[PDB]
Image 1: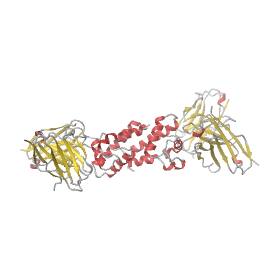
Image 2 (image 1 turned 180 degrees about the horizontal axis):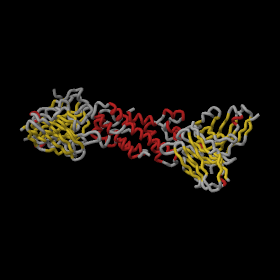
Image 3 (image 1 turned 120 degrees about the vertical axis):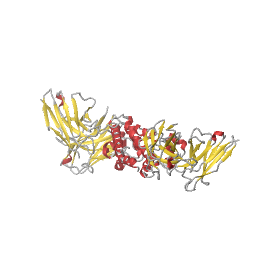
Length: 89
Length: 89
Length: 231
Length: 231
């Protein structure tokens, strides 16, 4: 039996690791692909725990569309969307 | 670092548990809720390892709209969309 | 196809007294949280009746003397204390994949829902029959209807099941092409039509419903329609 | 805000010889796969230079006799052997969260450029000044332009940063209200605006750039602009 919380925590961690690699590493073009996918799929943009790197990935064009404004980032958190997925929201 | 394959495997197992419990237990309302969220988010319907119960969720309207038909369920596998998510596709 | 093999073929026990019935499967009928093996009780004339669901869980109404256990491929039904009215044939049946299949059966000697089917039918070989199953006491249009075939003396054989909302069906490959399942939502009536009839098709055909969610369990049965093909 | 505490404040080693500078953060500056603590070297009259990035990785060209170590809150810079060119002031800096902050500094003592800035300035108290920082068009529009202040004798202070593509600007709360960052693509020039000028706005103001993806590292600097506020 898989725990909701643990698996959510693992997905979050996976996302954060990908988010970081996309900015701190021009090699990992796969990390950009992974980040762009989550952002499109979960309809979100970055993280609260990595608000500095999020503003960069926003201007790298990896977030979905509409905003592109740094003011909005605080309400586009992927950690929340990941929480909502495993909760049923 | 966190294992890309292991997390994908756990997310499937979580989904499979939600899919099963949504049908097997009549009023597992979060079970249904979780299943709907996955379907609507990942654009998919049931899994190929649970084709029997998948037809039962298809007809309970917990799958995405306009895709209702048992024939199509083979190409609407959520297991494949979970694979694509974590591999950036 | 998963093949369920029961043992013994038939059993007899005193009023006491442990009655134990096994069931083996071609492959595992179980997942990390459920199986997917169930037990039905049938007495002569009557339709089958669900006793234990998902290996261990007693159906509401069923006495505590009935208990089930098992996992993977091996399952066991236990009755203790055995009592005079427990005399019946007991079928194990899986609902893991399509097609659903029943065990060969084990006879035990001892030392507001209702589905109204059509009456008996006698027909020439080559002809076609249409059996009807009128439902009442639940929401027909949101339900799955299953059909089961039982030849004289022989066991139970799953034909297919149909969702009454849109009449989309899932057939047993053996009956796909011969049996046609349809539903009339206005009538609250399920239908099965059999074509190119043969002495081989001479059997009692049952009609069985599932729960609200479409859990793959045969909750309520009809009395059956005895079809007999002859010249 | 995160406070970075360096030690020692100054150091005199001979041409030998170990030099060990320490840097302690208020809270962790480390994720599961990175920190996020860096080391810059500044010689008199020049902009700072990135030596070690992400705790341990030497920037291209930096001698292997430089090494960086640490995790969480405690980080250490090691030079061995010390040579004449190491006579400078060493600042640690984090890029974990806004605002970016620097360490108090460690003066070591022995026992081609992009980003063109505007010239020196003397200006009255109460006035405004808009300091410029020009780059090549083509390089400009995707640039994250950072601004850093340095009062004579004192350390380094992060003002804010602006994205040249759309002029979207993040400010250090201490300068939000006093500093305005603007970027003009068709001048290829980024500007910093200082209002209500005071004697202690007198400093050298640097303009620094990041790598393509906006890796929060101050790669390219300018010469600085010497703003002095006086009557």
